[PDB]
Image 1 (spheres, rainbow, N blue to C red):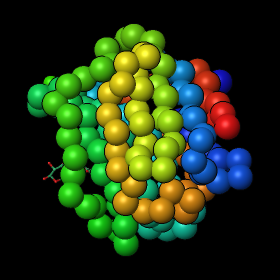
Image 2: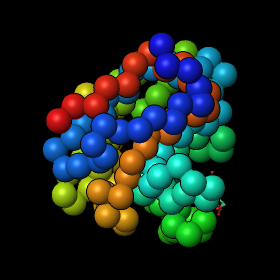
Image 3: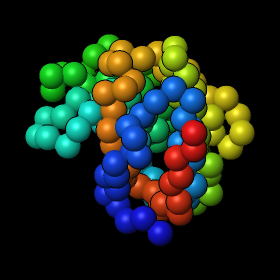
Length: 138
Ligand SMILES: OC[C@H]1O[C@@H](O[C@H]2[C@H](O)[C@@H](O)[C@H](O)O[C@@H]2CO)[C@H](O)[C@@H](O)[C@H]1O
Ligand SMILES: [Ca+2]
């Protein structure tokens, strides 16, 4: 099983039609975790899409982009699709318009592209979860 933090090159880079399958388990003691779609592996690399479930405060998920080391306008959904201790299936479908986020078969969010998606080279995952597998399809 992959170890954390996980920071992996996406084969051939990100492209439309690709789906990222993440199987994991949310920690019994989960505060946060994130999945980042990252542009390169340099100090201060841009993050085209930051997906950040949070139990601090109102349980929620935060979505954003980091460009030039600055966070953009945050998007939020005040709903939590994960559960402490519970296994989950997290899927990112890459479409021309947005990343479509699906959690346990349910559509959860559509994040509109801010950085051109072909810039993304790496998937990065860290925080309060256990990773079982990550597969790239398409
Ligand atoms: O937006 C993603 C980014 O959020 C940072 O925290 C934000 C916080 O969500 C917001 O409510 C507050 O106004 O500004 C904070 C600083 O930008 C996190 O620090 C970072 O890890 C990302 O998750
Ligand atoms: Ca809470």
